[PDB]
Image: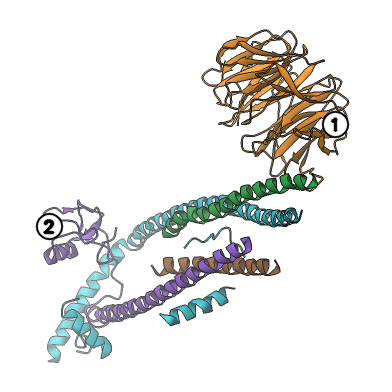
Chain colours: A brown, B green, C orange, D cyan, E purple
């Protein structure tokens, strides 16, 4: 369980890592318009 | 083994998310050109 | 399988599917129209008769209920796929009528391109002409616009022309092809239109309410011409994914809308391929070639 | 939950601090007793320190019988000798081989799993990039349609 | 080859018919006396159901310096020390693994909350770009 949990933790960490830059691009998109 | 079961469960879910985001914009394209069709039709009416 | 079909005495110029995807129609020099069943053994049930000239273009309606077929003998013909029998002989064309197109989802209406110097609009019920835009010269292919209110045509002067059915003037003229255009086919998008031209280049255009004013979108290499100057025709896939073309090189050219890469130059033929037909349902390909037979490729 | 490992090739400290703040938000028998006492106590139980030193007559005769038993136990060792050691050494190597065989099996199964996931992710990220490009073009198209509709309103 | 309770090399291996795994006769009988079920699968199992196996009569070479003194004094003491300290280290590792599991579950819940927040942020930013 420790191994599976650490794995899924870093995996879902990448989810926020991508989503944050997605929101970040969308913010400048809407801001420039 | 649990990593694949958690991956394959949500692999369609990561696909199912952008499916609508395309189709929500895809329907917006139809209404876009629908008004764009109305936008050209009256320009000739005012040109006339 | 490869499924090569035979039973035609001279070149087959036109082959296309039932818009059901149920039955097959092919035609050419032999002055008659053969029909087949697409599935099973690809077998032949019916043969339509009557056209004195060469069948230069056959065209379905969008349900599959009546058949349009442009003949060399100055005439178009609409027939009953129900029977195979003539309902109308569109006469009045003053020369070789090569191209025919029935209006889809609009009132029943037909545009025919001919070798007289006119494009002709006809209503099926009146036995009379609707409109006719004499530009100067032969028009070699004609297709409507999904509003059934512009009409696109391609001939010898390389500038693809489009008329508005209400103002009746040259609405949209587009330029960039180096030699004569031989084929137009508007995708089921109602927007993207495909143009073959024997200058060895194929082009993609888009008729919209608003276009960039110079709508030459995608360009592919590969098609050939030679001393034959046969009429070369193109099509989109049901999906707007793959473009299929034929050429006088015996190679079925299958390209993609996306990456414009050469997905296929398939051999197998003996004479020039004049028309490739996409199945409205399946990944099934039918090649009509001047080697007096057809091919049924599966991809 | 969904995260493309194969597709996402490209910040972890930032999200780590964010997770850190979000988490800052929210049977044996008496043998066991004697063993734990001897471990906490640690002092190992008193063994046999009688036999070797040699009251002393009995221990001495014990050393005599035990040295005789030991001198007998070294005869039956030298009788066979080095054959019995290698006879079990062959068994040792034979038991060793199966372990690495199963190790190979396990590596192969995990590798096939990762290969399947690789192709799955490769289809999926491609669909994702295509959808994103279509979304960008649709945004631009809505923008152009808006400009054209505004101009058409101008007439 | 091994016993599936004691981690030993059994001298009288017996295999169960409900879960086919070789156990030492002594530990398997004691397990059946404690509670009448299989250790591995927790399925119904009795002493009469077990089927003894026959084997290669596997041998251990007693060290050349083997006597009553070294067997009584040094050997058993080494065995008891290797038992006690190993059990103690295993208990300590079990406590540590429970602590690490707790920290992992908390960190996982925190990641879930952060992802839930970004799901509400990103999608509305996308809609606002569409607006």
- Residue C214, placed above or below residue C290: below
Q: Secondary structure at mark 1?
A: loop
Residue B8 visible in image: yes
* Dot 1: chain letter: C
Viewer-nearest residue: C273 or C175:
C175
Q: Which of E15/C25 is in front?
A: C25
In the rendering, at what x and y percent does residue C230 appear? Answer: 80, 21
| Number of numbered discs | 2
Comparing marks 2 and 1, which lies closer to the viewer?
1
- Please give the residue where the numbered disc 1 appears in the rendered image: C199
Q: Quadrant of residue D92?
A: bottom left
Going by the image, does E119 lie left or right of D83?
Answer: right
Q: Residue at x 26, y 68 (%)?
A: D75
Residue at 82% in and 23% down: C118
| Disc 2 from disc 1: Cα separation | 91 Å
Which chain does tag 2 point to?
E
Q: Quadrant of the C terminus of chain C?
A: top right
Q: How dense is the environment of label 2, judged by Cα within 10 Å: few (below 14), some, or many (20 and up)?
A: some
Residue D118 visible, this orientation: no
Q: What is the crowding at mark 1: few (fewer than 14 residues within 10 Å), some, or many (at least 20)?
A: some
Corner quadrant of residue D39: bottom left
Q: Return the residue nearer the eye: C143 or C298.
A: C143
- Tell me: residue E109, above or below residue C243: below
- Is B14 placed above or below E100 here? above
Decide if residue C222 is on the left or right side of residue C5.
Answer: right
Q: Which residue is mark 2?
A: E47
Rendered image quadrant of residue D48:
bottom left
Check residue C279 in the rendering and tell me which mark sits there, or answer none.
Answer: none
Q: Is residue C181 left or right of residue E45?
A: right
Measuring 72% from the left and 43% from the top, which residue is drawn there? C208
x, y percent for residue C1: 58, 24
């Amino acid at each position: 369980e420790l191994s599976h949990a650490l794995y899924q933790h870093d995996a879902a960490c990448r989810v926020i890592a991508r989503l944050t830059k997605e929101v970040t691009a969308a913010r400048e998109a809407l801001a420039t318009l | 083994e649990e990593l694949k079961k958690h991956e394959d469960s949500a692999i369609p879910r990561r696909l199912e998310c952008l499916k609508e985001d395309v189709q929500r914009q895809q329907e917006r394209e139809k209404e876009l050109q629908h008004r764009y069709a109305d936008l050209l039709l009256e320009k000739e009416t005012l040109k006339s | 399988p490869i499924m090569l079909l035979s039973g035609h005495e001279g070149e087959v110029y036109c082959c296309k599917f039932h818009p059901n995807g149920s039955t097959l129609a092919s035609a050419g020099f032999d002055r008659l129209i053969l029909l087949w069943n697409v599935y099973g053994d690809c077998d032949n049930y019916a043969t339509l008769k009557g056209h004195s000239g060469a069948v230069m273009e056959l065209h379905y309606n969008t349900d599959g209920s009546m058949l349009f077929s442009a003949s060399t003998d100055k005439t178009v013909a609409v027939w009953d796929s129900e029977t195979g029998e003539r309902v109308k002989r569109l006469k009045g064309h003053t020369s070789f009528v090569n191209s025919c197109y029935p209006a889809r989802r609009g009132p029943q209406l037909v545009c025919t391109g001919s070798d007289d110097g006119t494009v002709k609009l006809w209503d099926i019920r009146k036995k009379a002409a609707i409109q006719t835009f004499q530009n100067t010269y032969q028009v070699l292919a004609v297709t409507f616009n999904d509003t059934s209110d512009q009409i696109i045509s391609g001939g010898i002067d390389n500038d693809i022309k489009v008329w508005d059915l209400r103002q009746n003037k040259l609405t949209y003229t587009m330029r960039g092809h180096a030699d004569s255009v031989t084929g137009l086919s508007l995708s089921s998008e109602g927007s993207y239109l495909l143009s073959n031209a024997m200058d060895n280049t194929v082009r993609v255009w888009d008729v919209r309410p608003f276009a960039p004013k110079e709508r030459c979108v995608k360009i592919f290499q590969g098609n050939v011409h030679n001393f034959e100057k046969n009429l070369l025709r193109c099509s989109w896939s049901p999906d707007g994914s793959k473009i299929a073309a034929g050429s006088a090189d015996r190679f079925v050219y299958v390209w993609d809308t996306t990456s414009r890469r050469i997905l296929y130059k398939l051999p197998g033929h003996a004479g020039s391929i004049n028309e490739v037909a996409f199945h409205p349902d399946e990944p099934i390909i039918i090649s009509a070639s001047s080697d007096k037979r057809l091919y049924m490729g599966e991809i | 939950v969904d995260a493309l490992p194969y597709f996402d090739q490209g910040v972890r400290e930032a999200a780590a601090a964010l997770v850190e703040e979000e988490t800052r938000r929210y049977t044996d028998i008496m043998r066991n007793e004697f063993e734990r006492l001897a471990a906490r106590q640690p002092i190992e139980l008193l063994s046999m320190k009688r036999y070797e030193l040699p009251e002393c007559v009995n221990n001495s005769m014990a050393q005599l019988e035990h040295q005789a038993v030991r001198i007998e136990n070294l005869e039956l060792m030298s009788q066979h000798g080095c054959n019995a050691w290698k006879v079990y050494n062959e068994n040792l190597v034979h038991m060793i081989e199966h372990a690495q065989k199963e190790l190979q099996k396990l590596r192969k199964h995990i590798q096939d799993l990762n290969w399947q996931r690789k192709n799955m992710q490769l289809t999926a990220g491609s669909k994702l990039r295509e959808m994103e490009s279509n979304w960008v073009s649709l945004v631009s198209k809505n923008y152009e349609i808006e400009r054209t509709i505004v101009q058409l309103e101008n007439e | 080859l091994i016993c599936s309770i004691s981690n030993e090399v059994p001298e009288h291996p017996c295999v169960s018919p409900v879960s086919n795994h070789v156990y030492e006769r002594r530990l398997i009988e004691k397990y059946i006396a404690e509670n009448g079920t299989d250790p591995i699968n927790n399925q119904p199992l009795s002493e009469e159901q077990l089927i003894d196996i026959k084997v290669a009569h596997p041998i251990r070479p007693k060290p050349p310096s083997a006597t009553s003194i070294p067997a009584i004094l040094k050997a058993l003491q080494d065995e008891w020390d290797a038992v006690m300290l190993h059990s103690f280290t295993l208990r300590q590792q079990l406590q540590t693994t429970r602590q690490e599991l707790s920290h992992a579950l908390y960190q996982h819940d925190a990641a879930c909350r952060v992802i839930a927040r970004l799901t509400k942020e990103v999608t509305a930013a996308r809609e606002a770009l569409a607006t």
